[PDB]
Length: 425
Ligand SMILES: NC[C@@H](O)c1ccc(O)cc1
Image (cartoon, rainbow, N blue to C red):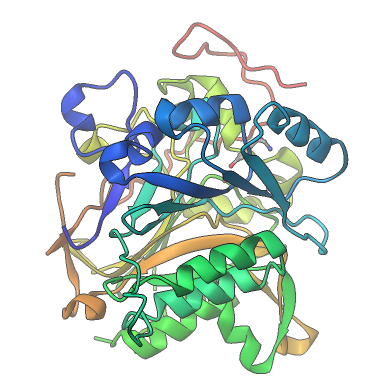
């Protein structure tokens, strides 16, 4: 398996659909390595739940929680952690308004080496229960023979890139993790790292983060040959008064770079209503009426969540993916799993007549490029050499009576899977 791309286990589907799937407990299990220390980067944390996900033997090993919480939220997190002497916190600086620390990553230091996990799940029970989520698992990275001179770098520059990502935090607790990564051999990594970090970026620095980073990698490591762009996410930012302010102008331009139809996949109200969770799935699809009403133009791009190939049409997506399928959707030029949803906050937005890239948030994803494997394209695995696309193709357009799930309005005409209505507030 060259890709090491996995979905999370979903409770309540036929076990066959969970065969190659992972729960966080599987990830932290002793069969993955003898744990010594870990860092957990995320957005939301349920600390009591998280510690229980670690096997009993590892539960007292040091854990660093990297979060973006401030004021009262920060206090509450510290209070969650207090009882556990082995836990430290690292508050990521968020100097730009409306930024979040949205990156989901595990750094897992073992006796036998190091593992990096980049994924899409918050560290709370419900994100790992009945949602479609994605996981990329690094190989076990060995320690560099303490008497030899090697970089431990990969052809995709993953090691240097992960170090620069962590360096942007400017955090003393992460310097230790940076030093740990220096000591390991990451040369077998076959993915590219795509990060977002809060800032306003100029000149050559534009290339470093967000959609400009993606554009840079597609220019340098893909070649060009009507191949659609597919975007799939669980949160939707304010994108502007029309398609030309951002979506089709700078965003699409990066995504269609190589060496044009745009499909966006986002649950309809009907997808949510009939899900395994019912309407409360919508708590994790925070598209607000205030944003939506400003941009009804976007919704003609929307397509339903459908995942029969992975038995997950009823498991609402919290995964975010972007990809470039051929016109018949039988193959792809690339695939990206990331924490970046569809917002300027996550991807970057051009300022000052296009000389400055403004990003609000921390985001992190891995890009699968066929060149990194010696190929020109990946064949799509039609049933979850060939890439495991976790939802159905081609994506199905919204019906005329479909609406995008919008979390802060009520749905009371029809009950959900559990016989409940949704009345937020
Ligand atoms: N802000 C907490 C909750 O609304 C939430 C948290 C994370 C998500 O990805 C979506 C929703």
